[PDB]
Each structure stands twice: as structure tokens, then as C-alpha cells.
Image 1: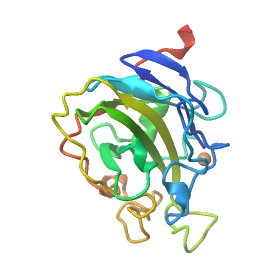
Image 2: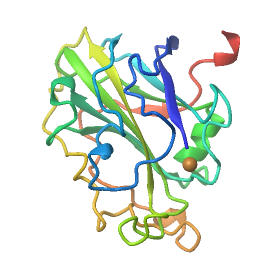
Image 3: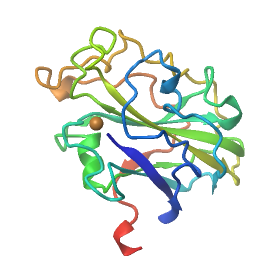
Length: 235
Ligand SMILES: [Cu+2]
């Protein structure tokens, strides 16, 4: 159970984004129904009043929390991957529009899941703003908790992979458009009962064998990190 509090741009906190520039759902419960319209941007997808200004190449940092800012972030049970997708804002997230900018699943070097490192990073993970056409975008940050993913939700609705999905409104101002955004995947649609990485038993299957759900990271993506960029405690 986790939510986005806000974003940082180049290590500068943009402030509380909840229901302001984040299309915040009413609570931190996961989406689990892979065919749900809730897979797009969680249960309360609507235009919120503010879009955060960035330029291509900026570091954009998502900041997650559990109950209060800079707390335990997410229950340590919730091992799994983190991804970030981008879609033009006019799509409202509908259709074949979601392009993956970031994937981090299980790090063999470190022996840790992305979520383990997200807790260490005080809820912070970052992407480099890609060189797409200037305009309004949705940045869909997605944590999959796999602690109950041995079952399909479709076979047992009390279990299944848990999607923590947050859509941030980001306006890209300065961009040379060196990597124009292609068509992407639909949410719901991209993940099905047969997709690799949706059904996974962390109790019996080694994390070293985990394959995160496609699609692959787009060739236009410039990278990211799971690391604390800003100290909320200094504010
Ligand atoms: Cu939870």
C-alpha cells in the first residue's frame, strides 16, 4: 500500500502534488484486475489542475509514501519491480499510447528488488525526461508487489500481483524532439494472465529467474535510478 506524494525536478521539490498534479486515487489500495479501466491511472483518472513544467534531460523524481510523507514508504513484504511509462496527455491514457521509460526488477549484483531499494531511497525513483515533442504528458509510475502473485487474481481475487499506479501531469517545455514518442501499449491490455512477470511465486521461484512484464524499455529512454535525490526532512 503506497501513493505518490509529489515529484522533484533536478533535486528541487515541486511540493505536495496530491489531487493537484498527481491524479491521486482516494487511498493506497492496489489495482489487481488486469482488464480493469483502473489499470490506466488507478481508480480516479481525471484531469487535475496543475501540470509540472520540465525540460528534456531534467531528472524527474517520483516520491512515494505509505501513510505519511517519508515514512516506511511501502510494507517490506511488497517485493517487486518498478516501471515508468509516458503517454501524451490528450490520450487520457487510452489506446496504444504507453511507452516504457524505465524498468528495475531484481538486481542480481545487490540481491535486492526495486521496491527494497525504493524503501532505502525514502520513496524516491527518477527518470531522465526524454527528448519527445514539447507538450502535456502523463508519467505512469507502476510498482508491482509480487508477495501474493503466485496466484492469478482471475483465479483468486484475494491474491494476485498488486499494481500501485500513479499518473503525474508533466508538461515538457524545452525539447529538441530528437526522439519522437512512438505508439505504445494499452493499459488495461498490456498485461494478461499469460504475461511473464504477472504470475510469480517469490516463496518457491528464485528472484534470479524473474522476467518483468513487457514491453521492453523504449530505445529513446535516457535512464533513471532508485536513489534519494532530495531530503524531505530539511523542509
Ligand atoms: Cu499493500
